[PDB]
Each structure stands twice: as C-alpha cells, then as structure tokens.
Image (cartoon, rainbow, N blue to C red; front, side, top):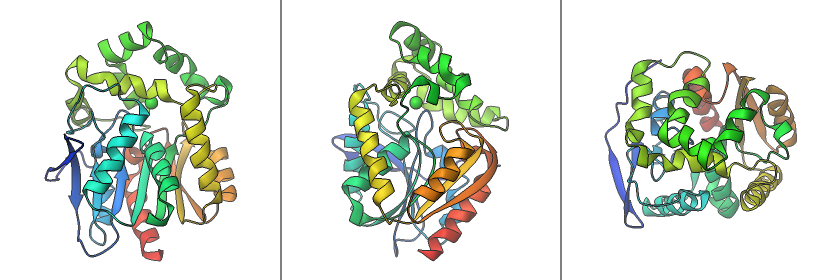
Amino acid sequence: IGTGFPFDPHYVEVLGERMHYVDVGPRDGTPVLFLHGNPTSSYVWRNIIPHVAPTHRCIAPDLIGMGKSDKPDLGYFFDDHVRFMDAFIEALGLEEVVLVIHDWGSALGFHWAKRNPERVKGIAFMEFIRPIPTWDEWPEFARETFQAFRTTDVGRKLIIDQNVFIEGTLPMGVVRPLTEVEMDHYREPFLNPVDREPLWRFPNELPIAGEPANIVALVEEYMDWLHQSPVPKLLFWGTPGVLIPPAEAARLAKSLPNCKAVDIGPGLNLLQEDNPDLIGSEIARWLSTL
Ligand SMILES: [Cl-]
C-alpha cells in the first residue's frame, strides 16, 4: 500500500481563508468529490484516487483547519465545516458531482446532498455518521474513550495536550499496522497543540445519547433523505467495523434505495487504509454504470 502523496497542491480562497485540495484528471465530465473526516486529510484518499483519475476528475479537499488548509481561529463546530465546504464547492464552480465520503466527511456529504439533491448523481460511502440513540449503540470497546473525549478537562488533556486522536485513535482504527511514514503524514497538520481544536470538537459533535441535539436533528434529517432518495449508492463495509457493523451494513443495503454493498474484508474505521485497491477499483467500475 502506497505511502507517498504524489499530488500537486491546489489552493482556493474560501470566505477569505485558503483551502487546499487535490485536483487531478480531465475536465470533460462529472467530477468525483472525496470528503475525509476526523483526524485525517486528503491523504486518506491517496491510493483510491489513482483508480478513478484516468476516467474522472478527482477533487479531494482538506477540511478547514486540517491537512494543508488554513487554520483560522474557529470553534470548528460542524457549522464551520458546513459553511466552508459549501463555499469550497461554489468556489470551484461545481455543478453536478459524485460524492465519495467517510466519517465526518459523510456528514458533510449527506447534508450537502439533502440540500442539493439535483446535483448529486451518486454517493459512495463508508463508516459514516448516523444517530447513536444511547451509549449502548456506540461500540463497546470505545465507550470509555469517547466518553472521556466528550469532556472539557479530561478530553482536552487527551486530545489537545497529548494528541491521542492522532497518536492512538487513528492507528487503532486501521486493522493493518500503519507505518511511521504514514503516521508522519497524518501528524503534519497538528504538530502545534493549538491547532488541534478540530480534533477535539469533532468527537464532541458526534450525535450520541441525543446530544448535541442540533447535530442529532441534522443527522436524522439526512438519513431520512437518504432512505427516500433514488440516487445510486455504494456502501463499503468491513468486519468488525466501528461506526457501521456488518449487520448494520447488510440492513442498510436492503433498506436504502438503489444501494450496492461491498465487503472490503477486515476493517475498523479507516477502511481506505486496509483495502484501497478494492475500494478504488469498485468505485471506478460503479462510476461506469452511472
Ligand atoms: Cl470524531
């Protein structure tokens, strides 16, 4: 699995802040927009993009405050990410798109799709954000960790001071052993502790046990939209997973309209790091059927 990031930097001014993005492939079709989550960047798509780039334009932004994008003084609430991603999409003059989304990137993607349904021609997704009614519906072995994350004193000591989301949570979400070189790519944006705000706010925005109520409502709304939409859907899943267990993936494949599910093999949260070639090749094949 490739550790390099052989992509020229592209930058666009978005609400007065510079955002970085990968942009490769031809301008003669429908672009494919790749959205990463927490605590990753466009680096997470590095081995998937090469399967798609020969036939379709691949656009992979770094969320505001992450990757090579600027780091404004924000709270980095989901509202901030929604605002900046909305403006990113408009700054690139995108019309219709295909979405490839993961983790907090899936919340952005589904929320954008709900509000712009005529402009989404397909959604590939994996390990995505859905409402978590109670802490019993959160993964058993990550309950104590994320409960600790969702506090001001303990959570910030862990995530901001000790950088545990990068040093611990990230590699623990990959079944195979992430290499030092790969870890260093993921570490790059957060070498300064003050820049780790998004890493702590994100888990505090997760819709768990009815809080934060506004996120729970937003996520419920786009899940309702997804269940009602005829848009082509491609769901990647792994065993045992984290956000999406195998049993949930099978249920979603039946319940969501026009949905194909693909087993990547062993996987936790960062499925892209465990089977990029299958994810890439299947997206490429799926795109040709659209
Ligand atoms: Cl998170």
